[PDB]
C-alpha cells in the first residue's frame, strides 16, 4: 500500500473511486485546488490519481511523478480530449469509450493504460450518457487499479487521430441536455453548416439579364395593355436611358427614385437605373405628398424618374427625367460598361405601418441574384411561362414578379388596378392569356382559389398566415416566408395536403434558419424560439438608421455569423420544415391566459360552412381584452353553434366572445386582409356574452359569488359550466367547503350532475341553513410528545423494514442563474425550517406507538460544491443518503455551482413533503428570495392528526370502511402485464421514461372531458384502464392504484406534511361499447371511491383481508397519479429526481407543464427493460390519439400495436418469401432414377432397393392404379405397415394421379368404417394380412399379390398439377371425430424445399422411417430424401420403441436426419449415455410436444456435433410451420417454437382479430403457401378455421387454437391450447415451470403437474407437504403452488414463538412456520422487532422476508451485551 494524492475539482470528495482505494488500505489525500510544485501534499506520495481536475499541474510535478500520475477521462482517447467530452462524443459522432491514461504536459495526450468501449443508445438523453460514462470510468478503475499499481499493464501509445475541445465551446448547445441522441443528431444535420457554402455569387442582375437577352432576344419580355416588348427591345431602351442616367451623375450605390405607375416604362426605368449603376427607389405615385418628400430626402435622391402626370408631386425636389421625353433616352442602344459589383445596392424599399415613420431597407445584387437563381430551377421557369406583375412596385413582391421570371425567358404581364381588385376579371385575363406562374399575397390568393382557373400551374403565396388549401384549379400551391430585410423570401413550402398550421417550409439556396432562445442558444427540435436568418438574403440594413440595423442584424456571439432577428416565433418540425407560431409580441391575455389568436381561426374554418376566418383581439377602455371571430360564410351561423363547434377542441378563453358574419373580407391594396376595416362589435359595452344569464335570486347570486371565488372569474352566469371554466377536482372540494360555511351541503357526485348554477340552485333551494357544518381545527396544547397520523405511521413502518432505504426520499432540483446569492437561498431555507413544525418534527416509538416530537430549532445541511455539467448528477447522487426519522430537519439541501448555473438541490422524506407541500415550499422560497414578507402560519399538522384520529371513531368512518370491504370482496381481477420473469423477492430498482403530449392534443383532451362532464383525470384514467386491459388479454375488469391529496380538513391546505392517501381502483372496460360509454363507467366507479377516500390504505387492505404474495404488491401492481399545473414559476422550474427507484412494478404520473402534459413511466428494471417500456409508451400514445379522435368508436376497434411495431414484426418473423421449383416429387424420383439408376434409394431390414428398381415397381402399380379409375384429386386409402410396399404404394398413388390416405392396419373397424365413409374413397391398397380388413369396401388390391401389379415398367405420364391433392391425413383431434386434412402438391413441395434449405439431405445422407404414417411427420421422412437424392432406411415395424434398434440404424446405415417426438428422445438419450459407437448423425428434428428444457443438455452430452432443432406445425399447415435451432451453451426459459419456414407467415391475434404485440398472448394463426385446401367433406369447419383476414389481404389464415406470444427476439413461444387453459385466481398457470422447479432436487425424479376441478367446479393444482411448499415458496408465486401434493429448541426460538403468537394471533407457532403464511404484514414485523428490542434481542425487519421462519431467523437476532459493572464501583469521600 502507498499514499495517493487524489485530484478532483468537479467530482466529489468521497467518490466510489476514493472509497475503493481506501478499502485496499491506501491513504487517499484529496486536494481540490491548484497544487504547487513544492507543496506538502506532494511529499511522501507514491501515486497521483486525477478525476475531473480543473487545473493544470506544473511541468515539474508531471516529470517528478512521471509514470505515477493517472487520470480518469470518460472518453475513448485520442477522441474527445479536453472538456465536456461525453457531449462532443455524441455531437461529433466520435467513437465512445472511457480511458485511464498517464498525464503529460498537454491535454489528454498520454500513454493509454486501459480503455473500454461504452455504447450510447439513440433514445438516451445526454444526461443519461453522462451517467453511463462516469460509471464506466469508475468501474474500469476498480477493475484495473491493482494491475496498474503492480506494473502488470504495459502502457501503449495513443493511436493517431482525435478531437480536442475546450471549455465554453459548448455554450451554444446548453439547452440540449435532456434531448435524446437521435434528436441531437437530427438537429445537427438540420442546423449545422454545410461544406463552405455552395458557390459565391459573382454576378449582378443586369449582367445576367444581358446574358438572357442574348439567349432569347426575340421572345416577348413584357406585355402592357395590348402592346409588347421583346427582350432586346427592353434591353436597348433601358440601355439608352442608362447612358443618359450615367452621364447625368449616377454612380454605384447611388439612389435614383422612380415615381411611375405600372407600365412598360416602369420596367425600362428600373433596368435603366441598374445599368447606369444605381439602385432604384420605388415611390408609389398615390402616396401622400409628405410620404413622397420623406423618401426622396431620406434616400438623398438627386434624380427622379417620373412622368408629367406625377411631376408636381415632387414640388421641385429632384432633377425630373421624363420617361416620355425622347431627349431623356440616348441614341446608344448598346450595353453600358459594367461599374457594379455583387455587393452593390440594387434597390431600397421602405417598410412601415408601425414604429417609426418608415425605414429604408437596402438590398444588394448578390441578394437578388441568389433568389432569382433559386427561383428558376425550383419552379422550372422556362421561356414558355407567363407571369403577372401584380404587387405594387414599392413592395418586394414586385421584385419576385419582375426579376425572377426575366432571368428565365418568361413574359411579364402588367396588371392595371382594374383587375388587381376584381379577382373574377383577373381569372379571366389569366385564363385568356395563359398565365402559368405568379405570386399572389395571402388574402388575394385565398379569394382567387374560388375562381375557376385553367392557366396557372404554380401559384405562390405568402405574407400573412395561409389557411385555405381548397381551390378551383389545377395549380400547385406554395407557401413562402421571408422578411423584407432578407430578399423577398427565405423558405418555401409546397402545400400538398390540409394542415392545421401549414409549414412555411425549408430554407432556400445559401440560406440557413436557426431557432434560438432568449440567450441566443440553439433550441431543440420542436421547441419554440425566435427565428434567425443566415445567408445571402441578408441585406445591408436600414437607411440612416444604424441603431436598428445593429439591433436586428447581429453577429452571433458564438457562431460568429451575421443573423437577422425576425421577431417571429417558430419551431422546426422533424421533417426538416419550419412552421410559423406567431410574433413574439402579438400575444394577448384573455381570462388571465396569454394566447395566440391565430390558433383559433383554423378550427373555425374547419366548420363546414365557413370559408374565410380572422380572429382579432380588441379591448375596452377598462383595459380588458375580448376576442372577436370574423367569418365569411354563405349565411349567418348561430352564436351557440360556433361556441359548440370550438368547444370540441379549444378551452373557454380561446373561444371568441363575439362572432361577426361577413360576406367578403376587405382586402388592403396589397392583398392582405384589412384588419382595421373589420366591423367593430356594437355590444362591446360589457356584454359578458350572449351566453351570460344573470343570477335571478339571492341563492343564484350567493352561488355565483362562491363560484367566482373558487374559479377566479368575475360575474359568473347561471349557465356557466364548472368544468368548462377551470373546474378541477380540487376546486369542486373548494366549492363544497365554501358552501358548508353558507350552510348548504353538496356532495362531490352531485356537482357532476349539476354542473351549472341553474341546476345547483334547484338542488339546494329546499335546503335550510344548518350551522356547524365547518368546525375549526382545534390547536393542540403543548405536550412532550404529540400524536402521529395514519400516513405518518405507515411511512414510519415503511422506513423501518430497510432503515437504510432511500425509496421514499424526495429529491428536487432548481437551476438558478449565477447572479443569485447562494447564502440568500440558505437563509430562506432556514426560515422555512422554523416556519413549519414538520421541518422540525421527529418520529419515535413509545412501546408500540409511533409518536412525534417538535424541536424548537434545527440546523440545516447546506453543502456548497463546485461541479461541471457532466458531473452535477454524480455529485447529487452521493448526497441522497438515508434519513433517521428521529433526527430533524428531515431535509438536506445544497447548491452545486457550475460555470453557467447554480443548481439548488434538496432531499426530504415523504413523511413531510408531498405534492401540495412541495408547492407551498416553492411559493414561500420564491417569496423569500424576492424579499417578500410571509404571514405566519396559523395551524399545525399535529392538530390535524388528533382530529382525524377522532374521526376514525365516528360512524362515517365505519360507513366508508364497509364500502371498501364490499368493494374488494370476492375474487379480485388479475392484471398480468407482459413483464419479465418476476423475481422471488420484491425488488425496488427502477428507471423512468417520459412521454410528452403536445399543447394541441392536451387542449383536445381537456375540452373533450369537460364537454362530457368529466375531468382530465377521469379521461386519462379511462385511457390507462383500456391500455392495461388490452395488455391483460382484453380483460373486462382491471385494478390499479391512485393517489389523493388527503387534505380532509379545509384548514390543512397551507401546511407542510404527508397527507396523500392511496386508493385501490377497481374499474371495468366494455370493449363492445364506445369510449364515451367507458368514460362514464370509470366515473361511476371513481366517484364512490372518492366519497370513501379517507380510509387509510393499510385498513383498506385489512378490510379486504388481502393475501400477501412475495412477487407482487398488495392490492395492485400498477399505480396512476396526476398532478395539476404549477402554481408558481419556481414550481414550474423544479425537477423531480428518481434515484433509480420504482416503488411499484409500473407507475404513471401525469404532470401539466408548458401548456402540455409530461407523462412519466416509472418502471421496475427487473420486470421491464429499455426496449420494453419504449414499446409501451408508444402504445399509450397510439391509444390516446385513437381515443381523442374516436370518442364514439368501440374500444375493441382501438389497436394496441403500432405501425412501427407491425413493420418490425414483419421483418423479424414474416419476411419468408423464397422461389421454389414447382417440379412435383413424383417427377423428381423418376428424374433421379433415370440419371442414377443403380443408386441405393430404400433400405429395409438388410435388403436394398435401387432408384431404378423402385421406380419400375412404382410404375407397374401406377399403371394398374390408372386403369382402376384414378384421376387427379382421387383418394385411395392405404392399409400397410412399414415396408418397401408402403413406399411403392405411396409413390404409385402419386404417379397414377390420386392422393394417398394412410390408415393404420391395426385400427378398430369402428374407425375405418368412419373414414371409409367420410372419405368416400373406393380403392384400398392393403397388404395381404389386411385385404379383408377393408371388408371388400369397394375395390381392394393386395400389395403383396403380383396380380395387383402390372408388366409395364415405363414411367406413367404426368397427370397432376401443383394444386392437386397429394395426401389426406385425418386428425382424430381431441373433442372431435377424425377430420380429413387435404394437402396439395405445391404445399408439400414448399415444406420439403424449405426443410432441405435448413437441414439439407444430400446424396451421401439418409433418413430414418420411424414415425407412424398416420402422422404428418412421417411424410417428411417419406419424401425428405428425394430432393437431395439421398436414401430412406425403413425401420422395422414396432422398433420405434427400442432405442437399441433406432441407434443401430443410425450407426450401420450412417443416418444423418432423424425425427424424434419428445418423450421418445429421453429414452433414446438414456441409452446413448453409456455408449460410444460412431455416428454420422447431423440433425435431430423434434416435434409433437413441448421440449423439456432439461432435454437440450442431455442431448448435446450423448451426441456432441449433432444439431437439435425444435419444430412446430399443425397438420393443416402440411407438416411443419416454424423451427428453432437450439445451441449447446443455452438455457431457454420455455424453449420457443421459433420463426416460420420459407413462404410461411404466422400471426398472433386477440379475441377481436387484431395483431398482438410482443409479450401479449393470443391465438397462433398460420398463412402462406403450404396451407391446407381444407377439411374433406366439412366446409362448415373449413370456414371456421380457414378464414380470410385483412392481415393476408383477403387471403386465408388457419386458426390453430394454440395460445402463443411473440418474443423480443421474434421467436414465437407456445403457451398451450386456447381451451384447456388453467388459471388460479385469474392468473395463468404454466405447469412446466412448477415441474421444472420440482425436478432439480435429487430426491425427486418423477414430477406429476396437472389441474383438478374441485368443489364448486373451481380448480386447483394437484401433484413432506409444507416442505414441498417451501421448495416452491421460493421461485414460484403463491398462485402456482399445488394445493394437494411445535418444537422450539433454544430459548430464543421459544421467545420468538411467544412473540410471534402475540402479534400474529396464532396460539401455536412452529420454528418452521412462514411469517406471511400466518398473517405476516409489514405492521407485524415492527411489533415483533420492538417487543424483541425491549428484551435486548435485536432483529431486523428486513430479515423476516429473507428468513420467514423462526429457525431461519434465529441465528440473525443478536443479543445486546449489557455492562453490569460501572466505571466507579467504590466511592470514597475525603
Ligand atoms: P380530479 O381532477 O378527477 O381529481 C382526482 C384526484 C387526482 C384524486 C384529485 O382529487 C387529487 O387528489 N389531486 C392531487 C393528488 C396528488 O397529490 N398527486 C401528487 C402525489 N405525488 C406526491 O405526493 C409525491 N411524488 C410526486 O408527485 C411528492 C413527494 C411530491
Ligand atoms: P407492508 O408489507 O410494507 O405493506 C402494508 C403497508 C400498508 C404498510 C404498505 O403496503 C403501504 O404503506 N402501502 C401504501 C403506500 C403506497 O402505496 N404509496 C406511498 C405514498 N406515496 C406515493 O405513492 C408516491 N407519491
Ligand atoms: Mn481530463
Image (cartoon, rainbow, N blue to C red):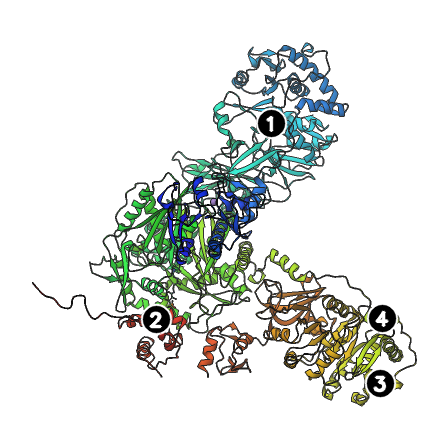
Q: Which label's residue is closer to the chain start, 1 or 2?
A: 1
As drawn, which residue projects farthest toward the right? 1351
Q: CA distance from mark 2 to mark 3?
A: 82 Å
Q: Provide residue 1198's location: percent of width, then percent of height.
A: 57, 60
Q: Classify 10 Å Cα crowding around label 3: few (below 14), some (14-19), many (20 and above).
A: many
Mark 1 lies on residue: 396
Q: CA distance from mark 4 to mark 3?
A: 28 Å
Indicate yes or no: mark 4 CB to ligand 2 under 8 Å: no
Q: Classify 10 Å Cα crowding around label 4: few (below 14), some (14-19), many (20 and above).
A: some
Please state which of residues 1631 and 582 is positioned toward the viewer in this rendering.
Answer: 1631
Q: Is residue 1390 above or below residue 464?
A: below
Q: Which label's residue is closer to the chain start, 4 or 2?
A: 4
Q: Is residue 323 above or below residue 752?
A: above
Quarter containing ligand 1? bottom left
Mark number displayed over residue 1341 = 3
Mark 2 lies on residue: 1725
Q: Which label's residue is closer to the chain start, 1 or 3?
A: 1
Mark 4 lies on residue: 1232
Figure quadrant of residue 1708:
bottom left
Helix, strand, or loop for circle 1? helix
Depth check, mark 4 against mark 3: the one in front is 4
Amino acid at each position: 500500500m502507498g499514499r495517493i494524492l487524489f485530484l478532483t475539482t468537479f467530482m466529489s470528495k468521497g467518490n466510489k473511486v476514493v472509497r475503493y482505494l481506501e478499502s485496499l488500505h491506501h491513504e487517499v489525500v484529496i486536494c481540490q485546488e491548484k497544487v504547487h510544485a513544492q507543496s506538502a501534499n506532494l511529499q511522501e506520495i507514491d501515486w497521483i490519481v486525477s478525476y475531473a481536475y480543473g487545473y493544470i499541474l506544473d511541468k515539474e510535478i508531471v516529470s517528478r511523478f512521471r509514470g505515477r500520475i493517472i487520470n480518469l477521462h470518460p472518453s475513448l482517447l485520442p477522441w474527445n480530449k479536453g472538456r465536456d467530452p461525453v457531449f462532443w462524443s455524441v455531437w461529433d459522432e466520435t467513437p465512445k469509450g472511457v480511458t485511464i491514461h498517464l498525464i503529460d504536459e498537454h491535454v489528454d495526450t498520454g500513454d493509454i493504460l486501459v480503455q473500454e468501449e461504452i455504447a450510447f443508445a439513440d433514445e438516451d438523453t445526454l444526461l443519461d450518457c453522462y451517467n453511463k460514462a462516469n460509471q464506466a470510468i469508475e468501474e474500469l478503475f476498480i477493475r484495473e487499479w491493482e494491475n496498474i499499481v503492480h506494473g502488470r499493464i504495459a502502457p501503449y501509445r495513443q493511436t493517431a487521430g482525435g478531437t480536442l475541445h475546450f471549455k465554453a465551446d459548448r455554450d451554444f448547445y446548453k439547452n440540449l441536455n435532456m434531448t435524446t441522441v437521435r434528436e441531437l443528431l437530427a438537429l445537427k444535420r438540420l442546423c449545422a453548416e454545410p461544406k463552405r457554402g455552395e458557390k459565391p455569387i459573382d454576378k449582378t442582375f443586369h449582367q445576367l439579364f444581358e446574358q438572357q437577352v442574348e439567349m432569347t432576344p426575340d421572345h416577348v419580355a413584357v406585355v402592357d395593355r395590348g402592346q409588347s416588348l421583346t427582350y432586346k427591345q427592353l434591353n436597348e431602351r433601358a440601355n439608352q436611358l442608362a447612358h443618359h442616367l450615367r452621364g447625368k451623375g449616377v454612380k454605384p450605390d447611388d439612389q435614383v427614385a422612380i415615381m411611375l405607375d405600372k407600365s412598360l416604362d416602369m420596367i425600362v426605368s428600373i433596368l435603366a437605373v441598374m445599368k447606369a449603376g444605381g439602385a432604384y427607389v420605388p415611390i408609389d405615385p398615390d402616396y401622400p405628398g409628405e410620404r413622397i418628400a420623406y423618401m426622396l430626402a431620406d434616400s438623398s435622391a438627386a434624380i427622379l424618374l417620373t412622368n408629367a402626370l406625377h411631376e408636381e408631386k415632387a414640388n421641385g425636389a429632384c432633377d425630373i427625367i421624363d420617361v416620355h421625353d425622347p431627349d431623356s433616352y440616348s441614341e446608344n442602344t448598346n450595353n453600358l460598361p459594367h461599374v457594379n459589383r455583387p455587393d452593390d445596392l440594387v434597390y431600397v424599399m421602405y417598410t412601415s405601418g408601425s414604429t417609426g415613420l418608415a425605414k429604408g431597407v437596402m438590398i444588394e445584387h448578390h441578394n437578388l441574384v441568389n433568389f432569382c437563381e433559386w427561383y428558376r430551377p425550383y419552379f422550372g421557369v422556362t421561356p414558355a411561362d407567363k407571369a403577372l406583375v401584380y404587387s405594387s412596385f414599392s413592395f418586394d413582391g414586385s421584385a419576385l414578379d419582375i426579376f425572377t421570371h426575366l432571368l428565365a425567358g418568361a413574359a411579364l404581364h402588367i396588371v392595371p388596378s382594374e383587375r388587381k381588385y376584381d379577382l373574377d376579371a383577373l381569372n379571366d385575363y389569366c385564363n385568356q392569356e395563359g398565365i402559368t406562374i405568379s405570386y399572389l399575397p395571402t388574402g388575394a390568393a385565398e379569394q382567387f382559389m374560388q375562381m375557376d382557373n385553367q392557366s396557372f400551374r404554380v401559384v405562390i403565396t405568402g405574407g400573412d398566415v395561409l389557411k385555405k388549401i381548397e381551390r378551383n384549379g389545377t395549380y400547385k400551391l406554395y407557401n413562402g416566408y421571408g422578411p423584407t430585410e432578407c430578399t423577398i423570401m427565405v423558405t418555401m413550402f409546397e402545400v400538398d395536403k390540409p394542415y392545421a398550421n401549414i409549414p412555411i417550409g425549408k430554407p432556400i439556396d445559401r440560406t440557413r434558419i436557426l431557432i434560438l432562445d432568449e440567450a441566443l442558444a440553439l433550441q431543440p427540435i420542436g421547441v419554440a424560439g425566435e427565428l434567425f436568418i443566415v445567408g445571402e438574403g441578408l441585406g445591408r440594413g436600414y437607411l440612416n438608421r444604424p441603431e436598428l440595423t445593429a439591433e436586428k442584424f447581429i453577429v452571433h456571439p458564438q457562431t460568429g455569423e451575421r443573423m437577422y432577428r425576425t421577431g417571429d416565433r417558430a419551431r422546426f418540425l422533424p421533417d426538416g420544415n419550419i412552421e410559423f407560431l406567431g410574433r413574439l409580441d402579438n400575444l394577448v391575455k384573455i381570462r388571465g391566459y396569454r394566447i395566440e389568436p391565430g390558433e383559433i381561426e383554423p378550427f373555425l374554418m374547419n366548420h363546414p360552412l365557413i370559408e374565410l376566418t380572422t380572429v382579432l383581439a380588441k379591448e375596452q377602455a377598462d383595459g380588458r381584452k375580448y376576442l372577436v371571430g370574423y367569418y365569411v360564410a354563405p349565411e349567418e351561423i348561430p352564436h351557440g353553434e360556433l361556441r359548440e363547434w370550438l368547444g370540441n377542441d379549444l378551452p373557454d378563453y380561446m373561444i371568441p366572445t363575439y362572432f361577426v358574419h361577413m360576406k367578403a373580407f376587405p382586402l388592403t391594396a396589397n392583398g392582405k386582409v384589412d384588419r382595421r376595416a373589420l366591423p367593430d362589435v356594437q355590444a362591446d359595452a360589457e356584454l359578458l356574452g350572449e351566453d351570460y344569464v344573470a343570477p335571478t335570486d339571492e341563492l343564484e347570486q350567493q352561488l355565483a359569488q362562491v363560484w367566482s371565488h373558487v374559479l377566479g372569474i368575475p360575474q359568473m352566469g347561471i349557465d356557466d359550466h364548472f368544468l368548462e371554466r377551470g373546474g378541477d377536482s380540487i376546486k369542486v372540494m373548494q366549492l363544497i367547503h365554501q358552501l358548508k360555511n353558507i350552510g348548504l351541503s353538496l356532495r362531490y357526485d352531485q356537482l357532476f350532475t349539476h354542473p351549472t348554477i341553474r341546476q345547483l340552485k334547484r338542488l339546494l333551494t329546499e335546503q335550510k341553513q344548518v350551522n356547524g357544518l365547518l368546525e375549526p381545527l382545534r390547536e393542540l396544547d403543548e405536550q412532550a410528545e404529540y400524536e402521529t397520523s395514519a400516513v405518518e405511521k405507515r411511512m414510519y413502518i415503511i422506513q423501518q423494514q430497510d432503515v437504510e432505504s432511500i425509496a421514499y426520499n424526495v429529491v428536487y432540483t432548481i437551476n438558478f442563474p449565477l447572479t443569485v446569492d447562494t447564502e440568500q437561498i440558505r437563509v430562506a431555507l432556514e426560515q422555512l425550517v422554523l416556519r413549519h413544525e414538520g421541518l422540525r418534527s421527529t418520529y419515535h416509538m413509545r412501546g408500540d406507538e409511533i409518536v412525534k416530537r417538535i424541536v424548537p430549532r434545527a440546523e440545516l445541511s447546506f453543502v456548497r460544491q463546485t461541479g461541471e455539467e457532466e458531473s452535477v448528477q454524480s455529485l447529487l447522487a452521493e448526497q441522497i443518503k438515508p434519513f433517521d426519522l428521529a433526527k430533524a430537519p428531515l431535509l438536506r439541501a445544497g447548491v452545486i455551482e457550475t460555470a453557467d448555473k447554480k443548481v439548488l438541490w434538496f432531499d426530504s422524506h415523504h413523511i413531510l413533503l408531498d405534492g401540495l407541500s412541495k408547492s407551498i415550499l416553492a411559493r414561500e422560497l420564491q417569496a423569500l428570495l424576492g424579499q417578500q414578507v410571509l404571514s405566519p402560519v396559523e395551524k399545525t399538522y399535529k392538530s390535524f392528526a388528533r382530529w382525524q384520529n377522532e374521526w376514525f371513531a365516528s360512524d362515517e368512518y365505519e360507513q366508508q370502511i364497509a364500502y371498501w370491504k364490499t368493494l374488494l370482496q370476492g375474487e379480485l381481477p388479475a392484471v398480468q402485464l407482459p413483464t419479465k420473469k418476476r423475481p422471488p423477492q420484491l425488488t425496488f430498482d427502477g428507471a423512468i421514461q417520459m412521454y410528452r403530449v403536445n399543447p394541441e392534443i392536451t387542449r383536445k383532451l381537456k375540452a373533450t372531458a369537460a364537454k362530457h362532464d368529466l375531468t382530465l383525470y377521469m379521461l386519462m384514467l379511462t385511457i390507462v384502464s383500456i391500455w392495461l386491459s388490452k395488455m391483460n388479454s382484453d380483460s373486462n375488469q382491471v385494478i390499479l392504484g391512485t393517489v389523493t391529496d388527503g387534505r380532509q380538513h379545509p384548514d390543512t391546505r397551507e401546511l407542510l406534511g404527508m397527507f396523500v392517501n392511496t386508493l385501490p381502483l377497481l374499474l371495468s372496460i366494455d370493449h363492445e361499447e364506445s369510449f364515451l360509454h367507458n368514460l362514464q363507467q370509470v366515473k361511476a366507479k371513481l366517484l364512490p371511491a372518492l366519497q370513501n377516500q379517507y380510509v387509510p390504505f393499510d385498513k383498506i387492505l385489512e378490510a379486504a383481508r388481502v393475501k400477501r404474495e412475495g412477487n407482487r404488491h398488495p392490492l395492485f401492481d400498477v399505480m396512476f397519479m396526476m398532478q395539476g399545473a404549477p402554481e408558481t414559476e419556481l414550481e414550474s422550474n423544479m425537477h423531480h429526481i428518481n434515484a433509480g427507484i420504482s416503488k411499484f412494478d409500473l407507475t404513471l404520473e401525469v404532470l401539466e407543464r408548458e401548456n402540455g402534459l409530461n407523462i412519466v413511466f416509472e418502471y421496475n428494471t427487473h420486470l421491464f427493460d429499455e426496449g420494453m417500456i419504449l414499446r409501451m409508451v408508444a402504445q399509450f400514445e397510439h391509444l390516446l390519439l385513437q381515443a381523442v379522435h374516436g370518442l364514439d368508436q368501440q374500444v375493441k376497434r382501438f389497436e394496441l400495436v403500432t405501425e412501427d411495431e407491425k413493420r418490425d414484426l414483419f421483418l423479424r418473423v414474416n419476411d419468408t418469401a423464397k422461389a421454389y421449383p414447382n417440379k412435383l416429387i413424383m417427377s423428381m424420383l423418376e428424374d433421379w432414377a433415370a440419371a442414377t439408376p443403380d443408386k441405393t434409394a430404400l433400405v429395409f431390414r438388410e435388403q436394398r432397393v435401387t432408384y431404378r428398381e423402385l421406380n419400375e415397381r412404382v410404375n407397374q402399380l401406377a399403371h394398374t392404379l390408372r386403369e382402376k379409375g384414378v384421376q387427379p384429386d382421387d383418394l385411395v386409402m392405404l392399409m400397410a405397415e412399414r415396408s418397401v410396399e408402403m413406399m411403392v404404394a405411396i409413390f404409385a398413388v402419386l404417379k397414377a394421379g390420386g392422393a394417398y390416405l394412410p390408415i393404420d392396419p391395426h385400427s378398430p373397424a369402428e374407425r375405418i368404417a368412419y373414414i371409409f365413409a367420410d372419405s368416400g374413397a373406393k380403392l384400398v391398397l392393403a397388404q395381404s394380412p389386411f385385404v379383408e380388413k377393408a371388408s371388400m369396401a369397394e375395390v381392394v388390391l393386395d400389395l403383396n399379390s403380383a396380380s395387383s401389379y402390372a408388366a409395364d415398367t415405363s414411367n406413367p405420364p404426368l397427370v397432376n398439377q401443383p394444386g392437386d391433392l397429394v395426401y389426406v391425413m385425418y386428425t382424430s383431434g381431441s373433442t372431435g371425430k377424425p377430420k380429413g386434412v387435404m394437402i396439395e402438391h405445391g404445399a408439400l413441395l414448399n415444406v420439403l424445399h424449405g426443410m432441405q434449405d435448413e437441414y439439407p439431405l444430400l446424396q451421401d445422407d439418409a433418413f430414418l422411417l420411424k414415425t407412424t404414417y398416420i402422422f404428418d411427420i412421417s411424410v417428411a421422412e417419406i419424401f425428405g430424401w428425394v430432393p437431395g437424392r439421398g436414401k430412406l432406411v425403413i425401420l422395422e415395424p414396432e422398433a420405434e420403441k427400442n432405442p437399441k434398434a433406432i441407434w443401430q440404424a443410425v450407426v450401420g446405415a450412417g443416418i444423418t436426419h432423424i425425427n424424434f417426438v419428445p418423450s421418445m428422445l429421453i429414452p433414446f438419450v438414456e441409452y446413448l449415455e453409456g455408449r460410444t459407437e460412431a455416428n454420422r448423425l447431423r440433425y435431430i428434428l423434434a416435434c409433437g410436444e413441448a421440449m423439456p428444457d432439461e432435454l437440450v443438455p442431455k442431448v448435446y452430452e450423448v451426441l456432441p456435433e449433432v444439431k437439435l432443432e425444435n419444430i412446430y406445425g399443425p397438420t393443416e399447415a402440411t407438416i411443419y410451420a416454424s423451427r428453432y435451432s437450439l445451441a449447446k451453451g443455452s438455457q431457454e426459459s420455455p424453449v420457443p417454437i421459433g420463426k416460420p419456414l420459407p413462404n410461411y407467415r404466422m400471426y398472433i391475434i386477440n379475441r377481436h382479430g387484431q395483431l398482438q404485440p410482443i409479450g401479449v398472448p393470443g391465438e397462433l394463426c398460420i398463412a402462406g403457401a403450404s396451407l391446407a385446401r381444407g377439411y374433406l367433406n366439412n366446409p362448415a369447419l373449413t370456414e371456421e378455421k380457414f378464414t380470410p383476414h385483412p392481415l393476408e389481404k383477403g387471403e386465408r389464415i388457419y386458426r390453430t387454437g394454440d395460445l402463443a406470444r411473440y418474443r423480443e427476439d421474434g421467436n414465437i413461444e407456445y403457451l398451450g391450447r386456447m381451451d384447456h387453459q388453467v388459471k388460479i385466481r385469474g392468473y395463468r398457470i404454466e405447469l412446466d415451470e412448477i415441474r421444472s422447479k420440482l425436478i432439480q432436487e435429487e430426491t425427486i425424479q418423477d414430477a406429476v403437474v396437472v389441474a383438478r376441478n374441485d368443489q364448486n367446479g373451481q380448480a386447483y393444482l394437484c401433484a413432506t407437504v409444507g416442505q414441498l411448499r417451501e421448495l416452491l415458496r421460493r421461485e414460484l408465486p403463491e398462485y402456482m403452488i399445488p394445493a394437494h401434493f411445535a418444537a422450539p429448541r433454544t430459548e430464543l426460538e421459544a421467545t420468538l414463538a411467544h412473540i410471534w403468537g402475540e402479534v400474529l394471533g396464532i396460539e401455536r407457532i412452529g420454528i418452521r412456520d412462514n411469517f406471511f403464511e400466518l398473517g405476516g404484514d409489514s405492521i407485524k414485523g415492527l411489533q415483533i422487532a420492538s417487543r424483541l428490542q425491549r428484551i435486548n434481542w435485536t432483529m431486523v425487519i428486513n430479515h423476516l422476508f429473507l428468513y420467514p421462519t423462526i429457525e431461519q431467523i434465529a441465528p440473525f437476532v443478536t443479543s445486546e451485551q449489557v455492562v453490569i459493572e460501572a466505571a466507579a464501583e467504590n466511592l470514597y469521600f475525603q
